[PDB]
Image (cartoon, rainbow, N blue to C red; front, side):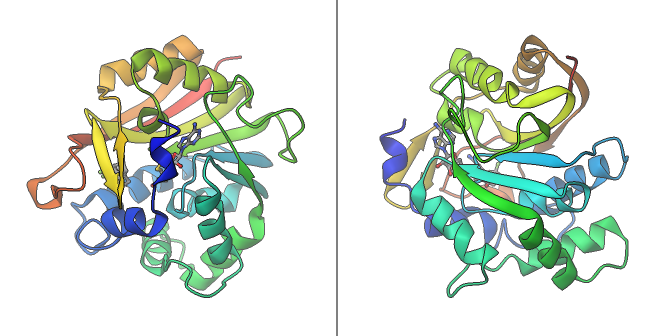
Length: 259
Ligand SMILES: Nc1ncnc2c1ncn2[C@@H]1O[C@H](CSCC[C@H](N)C(=O)O)[C@@H](O)[C@H]1O
Ligand SMILES: N[C@@H]1[C@@H]2CC[C@H]1c1cccc(C(F)(F)F)c12
């Protein structure tokens, strides 16, 4: 897998998944609004809080932290690929050619319903993200020996990482076990992923994915020592079915480590 991800094209990935039609946030019934809604509602309970937060396998995207950022002053983003960390860098620093997340920022504010403008939202995220670190979920210490990341983190977020980097269910489990070591007992995990997906494209790259189900995902969380607080499923409409992948649905999990 690590070899496959070496042809991964960030801009082709952003294009396939975060631009229209999937990047069209105008329809409430799309996968974008659904993801933002899950994240916004969860943080809106006020039960997920702290000082440090780590986003696992960020890739070139930031949407997964728009709702999160107002609850954690220290945010660490991560990814296996230098090209992704670079892409993240262009947006954090407002550099030339950065990807435009404004629609997602706008929708987050919309959905959070606190009358916040999207510039203040993006400003808070940029400010609270302290670092972008290399990571490998396959290592027992996914970050490494001495990472500048405050550990253990008060909360974890990861979207479309585990299943996308694991050849099978048992790898998925280990990878979960690994990243779980980074989470303080009682802390929270917000996990988003693909359901029953085997592949997706990212330019010239063809990534293999392990097809998992809601039940497999739940059972895996329990095994890692989590209490499943919430687990929802989004079924992928035909209109969002292109040739870029074969995802059947998307899951959202809010798990609390029972340490
Ligand atoms: N061994 C590994 N450990 C952690 N991340 C890995 C990894 N191997 C590949 N990845 C990364 O996993 C990411 C999956 S794509 C997910 C991007 C983003 N989180 C989203 O919500 O869209 C890729 O960026 C890929 O580089
Ligand atoms: N592997 C996942 C799939 C396919 C590319 C990655 C991604 C990013 C955002 C939404 C979705 C999808 F298809 F689940 F909606 C995906």
